[PDB]
Image 1 (tube, chains in turn blue, green):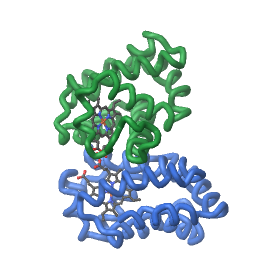
Image 2: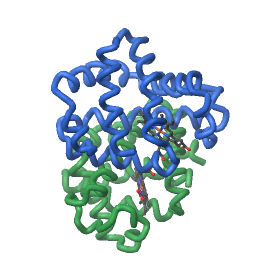
Image 3: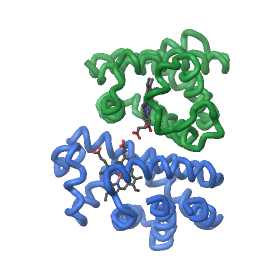
Image 4: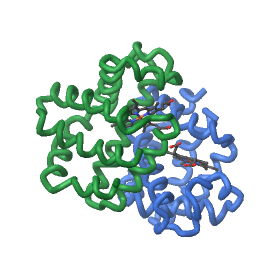
Length: 145
Length: 145
Ligand code: HEM
Ligand code: HEM
Protein backbone atom coordinates (compact mmCIF):
# COMPACT_ATOMS: atom_id res chain seq x y z
CA UNK A 1 0.00 0.00 0.00
CA UNK A 2 0.97 3.67 -0.06
CA UNK A 3 1.39 3.50 3.70
CA UNK A 4 3.79 0.56 3.31
CA UNK A 5 5.81 2.51 0.74
CA UNK A 6 5.97 5.52 3.07
CA UNK A 7 6.61 3.25 6.04
CA UNK A 8 9.73 2.01 4.27
CA UNK A 9 11.68 5.27 3.96
CA UNK A 10 14.56 4.76 6.40
CA UNK A 11 16.39 7.30 8.54
CA UNK A 12 19.30 7.34 6.09
CA UNK A 13 17.02 7.89 3.09
CA UNK A 14 15.19 10.71 4.89
CA UNK A 15 18.56 12.27 5.75
CA UNK A 16 19.65 12.23 2.10
CA UNK A 17 16.30 13.67 0.98
CA UNK A 18 16.51 16.52 3.50
CA UNK A 19 20.16 17.33 2.81
CA UNK A 20 19.64 17.54 -0.95
CA UNK A 21 16.35 19.45 -0.63
CA UNK A 22 18.04 22.13 1.48
CA UNK A 23 19.91 22.95 -1.72
CA UNK A 24 17.57 22.21 -4.62
CA UNK A 25 14.58 23.53 -2.69
CA UNK A 26 16.35 26.83 -2.03
CA UNK A 27 15.75 28.11 -5.59
CA UNK A 28 12.26 26.87 -6.36
CA UNK A 29 11.76 29.02 -9.45
CA UNK A 30 15.09 28.18 -11.04
CA UNK A 31 15.16 24.49 -10.21
CA UNK A 32 11.44 23.98 -10.76
CA UNK A 33 11.63 25.36 -14.28
CA UNK A 34 14.81 23.34 -14.86
CA UNK A 35 12.98 20.15 -13.87
CA UNK A 36 10.11 20.79 -16.28
CA UNK A 37 12.30 21.91 -19.19
CA UNK A 38 14.44 18.78 -18.75
CA UNK A 39 11.32 16.59 -18.72
CA UNK A 40 10.22 18.15 -22.01
CA UNK A 41 13.67 17.84 -23.57
CA UNK A 42 14.21 14.17 -22.75
CA UNK A 43 10.58 13.05 -22.90
CA UNK A 44 9.02 15.02 -25.76
CA UNK A 45 6.01 12.69 -25.76
CA UNK A 46 4.81 14.34 -22.54
CA UNK A 47 4.55 17.85 -24.00
CA UNK A 48 0.96 17.28 -25.15
CA UNK A 49 -0.29 16.75 -21.59
CA UNK A 50 0.71 20.31 -20.70
CA UNK A 51 -1.27 22.19 -23.33
CA UNK A 52 -2.79 24.48 -20.69
CA UNK A 53 0.65 26.00 -20.16
CA UNK A 54 0.96 27.15 -23.76
CA UNK A 55 4.35 27.20 -25.48
CA UNK A 56 6.60 25.47 -22.95
CA UNK A 57 9.68 26.12 -25.09
CA UNK A 58 9.52 29.71 -23.81
CA UNK A 59 10.88 28.54 -20.47
CA UNK A 60 11.11 31.14 -17.71
CA UNK A 61 9.40 33.75 -19.90
CA UNK A 62 6.22 31.66 -19.93
CA UNK A 63 4.14 32.89 -16.97
CA UNK A 64 1.97 29.77 -16.84
CA UNK A 65 4.98 27.44 -16.92
CA UNK A 66 6.71 29.48 -14.23
CA UNK A 67 3.61 29.44 -12.03
CA UNK A 68 3.23 25.70 -12.52
CA UNK A 69 6.90 25.00 -11.80
CA UNK A 70 7.05 27.02 -8.58
CA UNK A 71 3.85 25.35 -7.39
CA UNK A 72 5.29 21.91 -8.18
CA UNK A 73 8.22 22.67 -5.88
CA UNK A 74 5.84 23.39 -3.01
CA UNK A 75 4.28 19.95 -3.45
CA UNK A 76 7.78 18.55 -2.93
CA UNK A 77 8.30 20.89 0.03
CA UNK A 78 5.09 19.45 1.50
CA UNK A 79 6.35 15.88 1.06
CA UNK A 80 9.74 16.60 2.64
CA UNK A 81 8.07 18.27 5.62
CA UNK A 82 5.86 15.22 6.24
CA UNK A 83 8.61 12.58 6.13
CA UNK A 84 8.53 11.77 9.86
CA UNK A 85 4.79 11.09 9.94
CA UNK A 86 3.72 8.43 7.40
CA UNK A 87 0.04 9.12 8.09
CA UNK A 88 0.40 12.75 7.03
CA UNK A 89 2.71 11.92 4.13
CA UNK A 90 0.16 9.41 2.85
CA UNK A 91 -2.76 11.85 2.84
CA UNK A 92 -0.84 14.56 0.97
CA UNK A 93 0.53 12.02 -1.51
CA UNK A 94 -2.94 10.64 -2.22
CA UNK A 95 -4.23 14.18 -2.83
CA UNK A 96 -1.50 14.82 -5.41
CA UNK A 97 -2.12 11.39 -6.93
CA UNK A 98 -5.76 12.27 -7.60
CA UNK A 99 -4.65 15.37 -9.52
CA UNK A 100 -2.65 13.11 -11.82
CA UNK A 101 -5.17 10.26 -12.05
CA UNK A 102 -7.69 12.76 -13.41
CA UNK A 103 -5.17 13.54 -16.17
CA UNK A 104 -4.71 9.84 -16.98
CA UNK A 105 -1.10 9.77 -15.76
CA UNK A 106 -0.02 6.20 -15.00
CA UNK A 107 2.49 5.08 -12.37
CA UNK A 108 4.97 4.32 -15.16
CA UNK A 109 4.54 7.78 -16.71
CA UNK A 110 4.87 9.51 -13.36
CA UNK A 111 8.19 7.69 -13.00
CA UNK A 112 9.56 9.58 -16.01
CA UNK A 113 10.34 12.41 -13.58
CA UNK A 114 13.24 10.37 -12.14
CA UNK A 115 15.52 11.26 -15.05
CA UNK A 116 15.03 15.05 -14.71
CA UNK A 117 15.45 14.83 -10.93
CA UNK A 118 18.71 12.92 -11.32
CA UNK A 119 20.02 15.60 -13.71
CA UNK A 120 18.99 18.52 -11.51
CA UNK A 121 20.59 16.84 -8.48
CA UNK A 122 23.77 16.22 -10.47
CA UNK A 123 23.97 19.91 -11.39
CA UNK A 124 24.43 20.60 -7.67
CA UNK A 125 26.82 17.65 -7.34
CA UNK A 126 24.43 15.28 -5.56
CA UNK A 127 25.19 11.85 -7.00
CA UNK A 128 23.53 8.47 -7.51
CA UNK A 129 22.94 7.87 -3.79
CA UNK A 130 20.75 10.98 -3.71
CA UNK A 131 19.03 10.11 -7.00
CA UNK A 132 18.15 6.71 -5.52
CA UNK A 133 16.72 8.36 -2.41
CA UNK A 134 14.47 10.56 -4.53
CA UNK A 135 13.35 7.59 -6.61
CA UNK A 136 12.11 6.01 -3.37
CA UNK A 137 10.02 9.09 -2.59
CA UNK A 138 8.65 9.12 -6.13
CA UNK A 139 7.77 5.45 -5.64
CA UNK A 140 5.48 6.40 -2.75
CA UNK A 141 3.38 8.41 -5.21
CA UNK A 142 3.51 5.57 -7.76
CA UNK A 143 1.99 3.29 -5.12
CA UNK A 144 -1.10 5.52 -5.29
CA UNK A 145 -1.31 5.49 -9.10
CA UNK B 1 -6.60 43.81 -12.33
CA UNK B 2 -4.48 41.26 -10.48
CA UNK B 3 -1.50 43.53 -11.12
CA UNK B 4 -3.15 46.54 -9.48
CA UNK B 5 -4.24 44.32 -6.59
CA UNK B 6 -0.69 43.06 -6.09
CA UNK B 7 0.41 46.70 -5.98
CA UNK B 8 -1.75 47.15 -2.88
CA UNK B 9 0.69 44.98 -0.93
CA UNK B 10 2.82 47.76 0.54
CA UNK B 11 5.79 47.43 2.89
CA UNK B 12 3.60 47.51 6.00
CA UNK B 13 1.13 44.96 4.60
CA UNK B 14 3.94 42.58 3.64
CA UNK B 15 5.45 42.87 7.12
CA UNK B 16 2.16 42.05 8.84
CA UNK B 17 1.62 39.06 6.56
CA UNK B 18 5.11 37.68 7.30
CA UNK B 19 4.92 38.28 11.05
CA UNK B 20 1.54 36.58 11.39
CA UNK B 21 2.50 33.75 9.03
CA UNK B 22 5.49 32.92 11.23
CA UNK B 23 2.90 31.86 13.80
CA UNK B 24 -0.02 30.37 11.86
CA UNK B 25 2.27 28.65 9.38
CA UNK B 26 4.06 26.79 12.17
CA UNK B 27 1.18 24.31 12.45
CA UNK B 28 -0.08 23.73 8.94
CA UNK B 29 -2.08 20.62 9.79
CA UNK B 30 -3.81 22.08 12.82
CA UNK B 31 -4.48 25.56 11.49
CA UNK B 32 -5.30 24.32 8.01
CA UNK B 33 -8.03 22.03 9.29
CA UNK B 34 -9.23 24.77 11.65
CA UNK B 35 -9.61 27.11 8.67
CA UNK B 36 -11.68 24.60 6.71
CA UNK B 37 -13.88 23.49 9.60
CA UNK B 38 -14.61 27.14 10.39
CA UNK B 39 -15.52 27.81 6.76
CA UNK B 40 -17.93 24.86 6.73
CA UNK B 41 -19.47 25.83 10.07
CA UNK B 42 -20.09 29.51 9.30
CA UNK B 43 -20.89 29.09 5.60
CA UNK B 44 -22.73 25.77 5.32
CA UNK B 45 -23.79 26.63 1.77
CA UNK B 46 -20.22 25.99 0.57
CA UNK B 47 -20.03 22.37 1.73
CA UNK B 48 -21.59 21.21 -1.54
CA UNK B 49 -18.47 22.20 -3.48
CA UNK B 50 -16.33 19.80 -1.45
CA UNK B 51 -18.18 16.57 -2.22
CA UNK B 52 -14.89 14.82 -3.04
CA UNK B 53 -13.68 15.14 0.55
CA UNK B 54 -16.58 13.10 1.91
CA UNK B 55 -17.94 13.84 5.39
CA UNK B 56 -16.23 17.11 6.29
CA UNK B 57 -17.87 17.19 9.72
CA UNK B 58 -15.33 14.53 10.74
CA UNK B 59 -12.60 17.16 10.69
CA UNK B 60 -9.09 15.91 11.48
CA UNK B 61 -10.30 12.29 11.36
CA UNK B 62 -11.10 12.68 7.65
CA UNK B 63 -7.93 11.78 5.72
CA UNK B 64 -9.00 13.55 2.52
CA UNK B 65 -9.84 16.73 4.43
CA UNK B 66 -6.51 16.61 6.25
CA UNK B 67 -4.61 16.13 2.99
CA UNK B 68 -6.52 18.98 1.39
CA UNK B 69 -5.99 21.25 4.39
CA UNK B 70 -2.25 20.71 4.65
CA UNK B 71 -1.90 21.33 0.91
CA UNK B 72 -3.90 24.56 1.17
CA UNK B 73 -1.40 25.87 3.72
CA UNK B 74 1.45 25.27 1.29
CA UNK B 75 -0.37 27.44 -1.24
CA UNK B 76 -0.31 30.23 1.34
CA UNK B 77 3.36 29.51 2.07
CA UNK B 78 3.98 29.89 -1.68
CA UNK B 79 2.26 33.30 -1.75
CA UNK B 80 4.22 34.53 1.27
CA UNK B 81 7.50 33.45 -0.32
CA UNK B 82 6.71 35.39 -3.53
CA UNK B 83 5.92 38.72 -1.86
CA UNK B 84 9.32 40.10 -2.93
CA UNK B 85 8.58 39.70 -6.65
CA UNK B 86 5.16 40.84 -7.97
CA UNK B 87 5.65 39.04 -11.29
CA UNK B 88 6.10 35.70 -9.53
CA UNK B 89 3.30 36.30 -7.03
CA UNK B 90 0.94 36.99 -9.92
CA UNK B 91 1.76 33.78 -11.79
CA UNK B 92 1.31 31.52 -8.76
CA UNK B 93 -1.93 33.31 -7.87
CA UNK B 94 -3.25 32.87 -11.40
CA UNK B 95 -2.40 29.15 -11.22
CA UNK B 96 -4.43 28.80 -8.01
CA UNK B 97 -7.25 30.85 -9.52
CA UNK B 98 -7.59 28.39 -12.39
CA UNK B 99 -8.10 25.53 -9.91
CA UNK B 100 -11.04 27.44 -8.46
CA UNK B 101 -12.51 28.75 -11.71
CA UNK B 102 -12.83 25.12 -12.84
CA UNK B 103 -14.87 24.43 -9.70
CA UNK B 104 -17.12 27.40 -10.46
CA UNK B 105 -15.93 29.48 -7.49
CA UNK B 106 -16.58 33.21 -7.91
CA UNK B 107 -14.60 36.09 -6.41
CA UNK B 108 -17.46 36.69 -3.98
CA UNK B 109 -17.54 33.10 -2.76
CA UNK B 110 -13.76 32.88 -2.54
CA UNK B 111 -13.95 35.94 -0.29
CA UNK B 112 -15.94 33.91 2.24
CA UNK B 113 -12.59 32.64 3.50
CA UNK B 114 -11.95 36.06 5.11
CA UNK B 115 -14.22 35.26 8.04
CA UNK B 116 -12.38 32.01 8.88
CA UNK B 117 -8.96 33.67 8.50
CA UNK B 118 -9.94 36.42 10.93
CA UNK B 119 -11.14 33.85 13.47
CA UNK B 120 -8.04 31.67 13.26
CA UNK B 121 -5.83 34.75 13.56
CA UNK B 122 -7.84 35.97 16.55
CA UNK B 123 -7.38 32.64 18.33
CA UNK B 124 -3.62 33.29 18.12
CA UNK B 125 -3.92 36.87 19.39
CA UNK B 126 -3.63 38.55 15.97
CA UNK B 127 -6.30 41.23 15.59
CA UNK B 128 -8.13 43.15 12.87
CA UNK B 129 -4.87 44.75 11.70
CA UNK B 130 -3.65 41.33 10.59
CA UNK B 131 -7.03 40.17 9.29
CA UNK B 132 -7.08 43.25 7.06
CA UNK B 133 -3.59 42.52 5.72
CA UNK B 134 -4.68 38.99 4.85
CA UNK B 135 -7.84 40.29 3.18
CA UNK B 136 -5.60 42.27 0.84
CA UNK B 137 -3.72 39.10 -0.13
CA UNK B 138 -7.02 37.26 -0.69
CA UNK B 139 -8.05 40.23 -2.86
CA UNK B 140 -5.21 39.44 -5.28
CA UNK B 141 -6.71 35.99 -5.87
CA UNK B 142 -10.20 37.48 -6.16
CA UNK B 143 -8.97 39.77 -8.94
CA UNK B 144 -8.02 36.68 -10.95
CA UNK B 145 -11.38 34.91 -10.63
C1 HEM C 1 7.96 14.96 -8.80
C2 HEM C 1 6.77 14.64 -9.53
C3 HEM C 1 5.70 15.50 -9.79
C4 HEM C 1 5.09 16.38 -8.93
C5 HEM C 1 5.50 16.71 -7.50
C6 HEM C 1 3.97 16.95 -9.65
C7 HEM C 1 3.17 17.98 -9.16
C8 HEM C 1 2.12 18.58 -9.86
C9 HEM C 1 1.26 19.61 -9.33
C10 HEM C 1 1.33 20.23 -7.94
C11 HEM C 1 0.37 19.90 -10.30
C12 HEM C 1 -0.81 20.86 -10.25
C13 HEM C 1 -2.09 20.09 -9.95
C14 HEM C 1 -3.33 20.90 -10.25
O1 HEM C 1 -3.37 22.09 -9.87
O2 HEM C 1 -4.27 20.35 -10.86
C15 HEM C 1 0.66 19.06 -11.43
C16 HEM C 1 -0.07 19.06 -12.63
C17 HEM C 1 0.14 18.19 -13.69
N1 HEM C 1 1.09 17.19 -13.71
FE1 HEM C 1 2.49 16.81 -12.33
N2 HEM C 1 3.87 16.39 -10.91
C18 HEM C 1 4.93 15.51 -11.02
C19 HEM C 1 5.20 14.70 -12.13
C20 HEM C 1 4.44 14.67 -13.31
C21 HEM C 1 4.76 13.85 -14.47
C22 HEM C 1 6.03 13.02 -14.62
C23 HEM C 1 3.75 14.07 -15.39
C24 HEM C 1 3.58 13.55 -16.69
C25 HEM C 1 4.31 12.52 -17.34
C26 HEM C 1 2.84 15.01 -14.79
C27 HEM C 1 1.69 15.52 -15.42
C28 HEM C 1 0.90 16.55 -14.93
C29 HEM C 1 -0.14 17.19 -15.68
C30 HEM C 1 -0.57 16.83 -17.10
C31 HEM C 1 -0.61 18.19 -14.92
C32 HEM C 1 -1.67 19.20 -15.33
C33 HEM C 1 -1.06 20.48 -15.87
C34 HEM C 1 -2.11 21.54 -16.14
O3 HEM C 1 -2.92 21.35 -17.07
O4 HEM C 1 -2.12 22.56 -15.42
N3 HEM C 1 3.28 15.40 -13.53
N4 HEM C 1 1.72 18.23 -11.14
C1 HEM D 1 -7.03 31.34 1.29
C2 HEM D 1 -7.99 30.73 0.42
C3 HEM D 1 -7.89 29.53 -0.28
C4 HEM D 1 -6.78 28.84 -0.69
C5 HEM D 1 -5.31 29.21 -0.50
C6 HEM D 1 -7.23 27.68 -1.42
C7 HEM D 1 -6.39 26.67 -1.90
C8 HEM D 1 -6.82 25.50 -2.51
C9 HEM D 1 -5.95 24.47 -3.02
C10 HEM D 1 -4.43 24.48 -2.99
C11 HEM D 1 -6.74 23.52 -3.59
C12 HEM D 1 -6.28 22.27 -4.35
C13 HEM D 1 -6.41 22.49 -5.85
C14 HEM D 1 -6.47 21.19 -6.62
O1 HEM D 1 -5.62 20.31 -6.37
O2 HEM D 1 -7.37 21.04 -7.48
C15 HEM D 1 -8.11 23.97 -3.44
C16 HEM D 1 -9.22 23.25 -3.88
C17 HEM D 1 -10.54 23.68 -3.78
N1 HEM D 1 -10.95 24.90 -3.25
FE1 HEM D 1 -9.79 26.30 -2.39
N2 HEM D 1 -8.63 27.66 -1.49
C18 HEM D 1 -9.05 28.78 -0.77
C19 HEM D 1 -10.40 29.15 -0.57
C20 HEM D 1 -11.50 28.50 -1.13
C21 HEM D 1 -12.89 28.87 -0.92
C22 HEM D 1 -13.34 30.02 -0.01
C23 HEM D 1 -13.68 28.00 -1.64
C24 HEM D 1 -15.08 27.94 -1.79
C25 HEM D 1 -16.08 28.69 -1.06
C26 HEM D 1 -12.76 27.08 -2.28
C27 HEM D 1 -13.17 25.95 -3.02
C28 HEM D 1 -12.33 24.91 -3.41
C29 HEM D 1 -12.78 23.65 -3.97
C30 HEM D 1 -14.22 23.25 -4.26
C31 HEM D 1 -11.70 22.90 -4.21
C32 HEM D 1 -11.69 21.48 -4.75
C33 HEM D 1 -11.66 20.45 -3.64
C34 HEM D 1 -11.57 19.04 -4.16
O3 HEM D 1 -12.55 18.56 -4.77
O4 HEM D 1 -10.51 18.40 -3.97
N3 HEM D 1 -11.43 27.37 -1.94
N4 HEM D 1 -8.15 25.20 -2.78
